[PDB]
Image: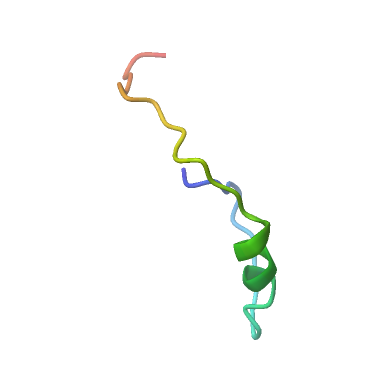
Length: 40
């Protein structure tokens, strides 16, 4: 899971949204779980 669920159909002829998203995005450096679980 990157961050996007559900199979959605799209046809970026521009990748136009990607342009704005690239700037809209924000870092600082991560966030992720160091240890991965199996049970649940």
